[PDB]
Amino acid sequence: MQIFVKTLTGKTITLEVEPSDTIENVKAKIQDKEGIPPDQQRLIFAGKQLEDGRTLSDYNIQKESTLHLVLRLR
Amino acid sequence: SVPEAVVNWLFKVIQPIYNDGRTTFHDSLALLDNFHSLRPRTRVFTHSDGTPQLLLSIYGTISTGSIPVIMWVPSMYPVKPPFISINLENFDMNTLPIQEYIDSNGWIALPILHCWDPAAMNLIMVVQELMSLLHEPPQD
Image (cartoon, rainbow over all chains, first blue to last red; front, side, top):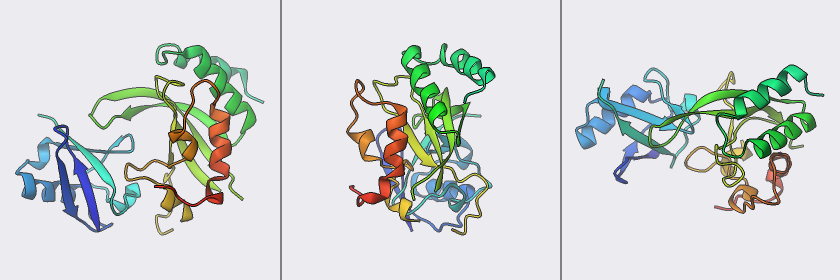
């Protein structure tokens, strides 16, 4: 299953995922492609900030969905 | 039809949020009066750019013959149209024809929302269109 992750700089990212993939696994995949540490990542979809422990399936995220990423320093 | 405690609360939370509080209040109250299966609450909406914003949302089940939805009313309503998502809350994810109408951003692609005229449309009409969504094939 393919999904997209859009960034603030208009940049877009393509990821290969499964519906059972957790948000944490998705952040790990983003780190692999962009080198961004998971701790700086905030993923947002349909008005909600996604929780690391939940899965894509839990948010009804389907193929071709577009998630938004914003980075924050804790 | 609508408890006065709800009417008063509705007027209250709308004032500091909406640019057009009179229209938002009129349209949202009319909606609650027409569809008893819908309820209101405010919740923090997180925008794509990360900005949090407290907004009024209306939620509940709508008949199509049924689907649980969450409708958000943007602070610029009616200049900007409302937006609706299927309400996954408490469902056994092991489940829809409605899915073919959900855009990549997770919103229900209701035609009326893309062909929006802020001077002749309201929230009630939006729900009405949702009730007939399956009568036409998914556009884009």
